[PDB]
Image (cartoon, coloured by chain):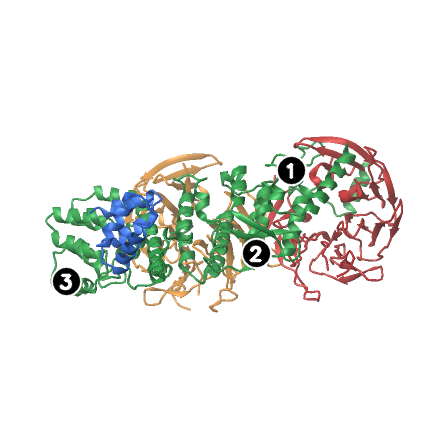
Chain colours: A red, B orange, C green, D blue
Amino acid sequence: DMIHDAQMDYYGTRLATCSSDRSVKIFDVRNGGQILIADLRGHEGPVWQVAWAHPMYGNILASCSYDRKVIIWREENGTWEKSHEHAGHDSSVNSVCWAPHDYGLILACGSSDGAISLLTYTGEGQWEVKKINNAHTIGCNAVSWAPAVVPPSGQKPNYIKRFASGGCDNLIKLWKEEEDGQWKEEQKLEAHSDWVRDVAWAPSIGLPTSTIASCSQDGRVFIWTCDDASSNTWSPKLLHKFNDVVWHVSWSITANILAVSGGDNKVTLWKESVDGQWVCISDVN
Amino acid sequence: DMIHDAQMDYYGTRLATCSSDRSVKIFDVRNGGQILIADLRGHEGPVWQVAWAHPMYGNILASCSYDRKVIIWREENGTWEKSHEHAGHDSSVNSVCWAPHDYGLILACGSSDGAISLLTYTGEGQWEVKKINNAHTIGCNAVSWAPAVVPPSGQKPNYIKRFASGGCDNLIKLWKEEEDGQWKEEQKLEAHSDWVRDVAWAPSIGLPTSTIASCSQDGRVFIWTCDDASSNTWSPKLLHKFNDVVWHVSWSITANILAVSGGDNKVTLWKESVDGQWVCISDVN
Amino acid sequence: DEIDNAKLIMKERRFTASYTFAKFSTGSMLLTKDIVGKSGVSIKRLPTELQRKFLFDDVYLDKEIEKVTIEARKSNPYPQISESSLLFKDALDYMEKTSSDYNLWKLSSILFDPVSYPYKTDNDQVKMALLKKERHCRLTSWIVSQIGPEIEEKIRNSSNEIEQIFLYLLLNDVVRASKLAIESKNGHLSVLISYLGSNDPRIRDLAELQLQKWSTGGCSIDKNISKIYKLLSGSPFEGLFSLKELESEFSWLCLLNLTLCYGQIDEYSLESLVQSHLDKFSLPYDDPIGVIFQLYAANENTEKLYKEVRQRTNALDVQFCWYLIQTLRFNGTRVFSKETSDEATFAFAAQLEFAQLHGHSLFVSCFLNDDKAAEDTIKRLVMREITLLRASTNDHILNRLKIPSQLIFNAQALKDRYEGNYL
Amino acid sequence: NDVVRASKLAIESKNGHLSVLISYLGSNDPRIRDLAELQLQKWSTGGCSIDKNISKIYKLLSG
């Protein structure tokens, strides 16, 4: 009936999908034509978001759900079996996301109980899970990774390993991997008057002026611009407000165009003008 | 082919229209069905805007045009003849408007030569024309009347008789009938980066917080406001900016809903929220 | 029995039946939900509003590449442009002589593309004066063609021969303007017209000094005989009998041609000259040939005006802006800031990405100063579209762009690897 | 004595430098004059490979 989230594969070859019928369908798109390939069923509740891991680790795809469990489906010659599962949270799991391929193969999941698990991968079918309790007050909805940024020796750098995340408390808390091993909330961002729906960490076009977008029940979309001259100073700026909720927000790769999904079943595109005010480039559908 | 402006009659009975073919057509809408009634032809150039006078003066309708002339068509038993004409400007006449019915039967016209005529009516077929030269630098596009506001004796009050007006210089100059007899520019409003297209003096819902809307080539819509009676303070506030020009702006009567015409052949509606920020209530068409 | 959870969860989740969604993907395509997909995933794509035909033919990209010299950057093996003999001129061939583009381009090619003697004489006082002039004619000679239809035809309309002459002057055609003068028994003019081309104060004053006298009880004089002497005075628009009145029916460009031919008010730089005209006259809105002049006119303030200009007009085509900055930057022609250059290099290299023409993207990508960013993009672009940049796009683009041996092998290996399981 | 058309042709044939001299032709500037003649003298040494026309024209500048 109704799908929730669906994301294209890297190298634009597949297209995983999931709807409230608890079915994770992987469709192939060669030449523009859709063609199913498997219907990975396995959630006791509707699937929420879904994300493809980086081809550098073979072919992996994870899906979270209202069943409080998250699944990771590997692939070995057409063998789409699940190599690992993780039910570390008590309430539904609104979102998942993968850490930039350099950090390794880390997966971030925000539940509705107000927590956040982080599955790191080891040599074999093993997965450690550094968890974050009471991250948001009433639960969490969004989880986005901060772009992989590189900081005289034979070493692959230690990254700042940050990742933002909105929730039901209205706060968009940023996070950071403390040198010792666990994450801490580097900062809070309270600009929304109701539930934060989605939070997307725009990719850095090599440019140091890292941005982040958010949309919430209040129907406003903010763009937290930040000049981190070593101190957390995130100055929100209003994109627009619709009389209805905004459900999703995503960044187009090159221009940094924002796809604003929400309101009237319509989706909008935006680009920040040479003037600083963001504009709507067009109406989708 | 393409119409320009068309305005419904008071008492919602007729519907005058004009298009670039120099034809001023008066339709009639009883029950929702359109039915022509006369095609008043008479302009050497396309007709621009058109306005219906107040039924208190019989049935009058004036239309300006690129022909540098403005026409006033009376009506006597179906006799739609023109009782007066006025070619007091050298360049085209972008707009016309009638002064609130209490001031009398005054008509304001802004030309493209940068002037502004004001036809007042007398006892018979006579019309004096107090004119304003070099009102705007490159010409004028909009002309809107300020709502008739009433200030122990047998007298019909002397009103502040103001009327705003945008133009090609980007300035939205307000105006006022000096006690002696001529109008003077009470104030300028420079917030637009290009030609001001239209300027509409929102009607006061009895409320003293008089407002005014404007739209220009830059593609921004401002709702200039005055916090109190008698304080020369007009603080503009941005409604929205589209990547394309906005052609017209009109006020809905009760709610003060703004109909924003311009951009992508689309027209939008806006209502100022209980929060102060303006929102789009819906998309027309 | 199964609908109450959909209701409970739809509700225990603040989810209206209005919930929609959309997300851009790696290739730069967005997935809207429409019911038009086997699974309701309208994979629409992103429009490259970049309208200019030649961009889709190998030849241009291929040929325009030999126009450059690539060299790995100072902080990594990622190639960046060292030298580029790129001129507006280049582009002309691939366009058509009737389009406004050809004009905009042909114009720039004149205002900015370098001028040059074709023989080695070195009195720098001379060579510098020639090029000074070569550029002069070149430009007026152009406007003469742009106002050709305009004036030529406006001449068929005249019963007055004297007015006819003034018109021929307006086209910088002295030879015919003179012939007419003699043939109408209005010779004295053929004399002045003779002097017109030069700069002799005797005349200049003789003209003006006369003009002043002509305002004292001496009427029945043609506006044309006057307008003409005015053309001798020197500055015709800021005069005692000004021509500022012509703004009525003459293309602003018609006027400009005047200030550039008879308006040599002072003997200085052209750029500044052009600029003088702009001061007395307002320009055509939304006009690309117009803007381009302001850019030429505002010499040192070049980048400042550009910024100022782009903030108000969509008349200048992304690809143009870029080609401008670039041709101007690699010829010393003007003053352009690294921040602003790369700022507009991304712009273009992006449109080229939505169009999928990666070959172009990668190439424009080398016009990046920020070695981090360059590497950053290149690694990305290539890692995702290797197959596309291989076997037939001309068979080597990547070696041609002095791209890293490793990156190729790496990203290559990665996909073969990817396709490996898919099979 | 048709400079206007003589010039137009010069530019239109990708032989612009002439349109420049042609510009000066009508006046009397020694710079040019000499530039012309001084060149002419050089053109008689080893390099006799130019149009008789480009030459004839510079000749019109010499005086």
Which chain does the residue under circle 2 lie in?
A: A
The amino acid marked with disc number 2 is Gln
Residue at 52% in and 50% down? B243
Which chain does the residue under circle 3 lie in?
A: C
| Front residue (pair C139, A112) | C139
Q: Is residue A28 above or below residue C67?
A: above
**Which mark is in front, 2 or 3?**
3
Same chain for mark 2 and mark 3? The answer is no
Residue at 19% in and 44% down? C158
For residue B59, say whether it is visible. yes
Q: Residue C169 placed where, x, y %?
A: 23, 51
| Front residue (pair C3, A119) | A119
On the image, numbered disc 2 is attached to which residue?
A277
The amino acid marked with disc number 1 is Arg
Element type where label 2 sits in the image: loop
On the image, numbered disc 3 is attached to which residue?
C214
Answer with left or right where residue A80 lies relative to residue B285: right
On the image, numbered disc 1 is attached to which residue?
C390
Answer with left or right where residue A17 lies relative to residue B67: right
For residue B282, say whether it is visible. no
